Image 1 (cartoon, one colour):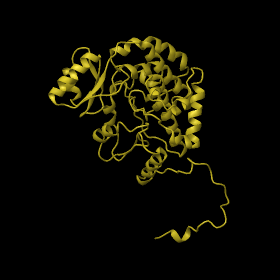
Image 2 (tube, rainbow, N blue to C red):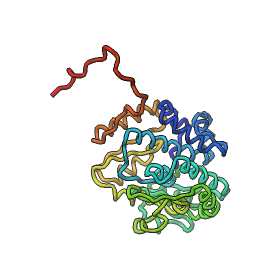
Image 3 (cartoon, rainbow, N blue to C red):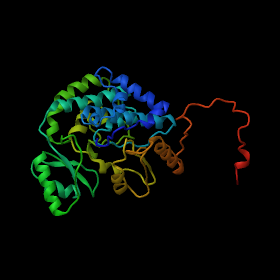
Image 4 (spheres, rainbow, N blue to C red):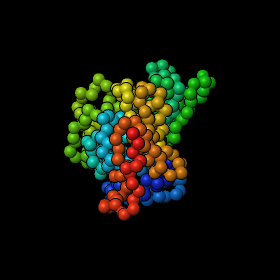
Length: 338
């Protein structure tokens, strides 16, 4: 969450595959009155205020990007998610279908909206995970283990704000991310669990096994043999929504000399990956906020993928060119230099 910007994904709509994927997501989420394309097109800034639209559109854009990547043949070797994003990770790994993933995202948003819980702010602080948790005032818990250097804390609005101000008095890094006014992964989210569990059981019918490629971030490492971590059921989603995100813990498992692609409508976690991932790895955004035309940025990402040794054919993205080729096409033999 947190990487939703006005007009996200409009440039990619021109590509046939991405537009078809967005239409499929819309048809998936038709009964609830949400039209993904309509949400993307709306110009008013209010569209992203309601968390339902934000979550649904974010998941849809990630699914569309994964469809684009899979079109060229790129098969991921690993997968790491962050808060909501396991659903996108679920689809990328293959444990979930597009309809099921979009339904899960929308019902997460719906359940969270129904909560009507007291406002609780979640902000990031520059202190360390171990040190901060002791320093956390009662009722406030670290939000996400982004990295050793930077960690975010989520909790009740008043305690979070007071602690952030005191830390600023301490000079440490202070920032409250736009979280729709609701704290996340705290005991506050525990209220929404039952209805979410029942609705997701109604949504997901036949859970399927997880893969070794996927590295769950809602379950500590030692527990990867548990029943919840085995398959992506309602328990997996609830755990990913309740417990804090162990984003950094999964980065220690990234082998040296690896290509890391940020599947998101904004490479927010680029700094976290750069600092907490081994220097040998390369980071590629695949999309940026308020860029003039995101198709160029996606093509630049694919080009950097080409430069890094990973084969990817950009022909699949665009419509096929009919052969035989037109008479008079420039010769290719003279260009090959040895």
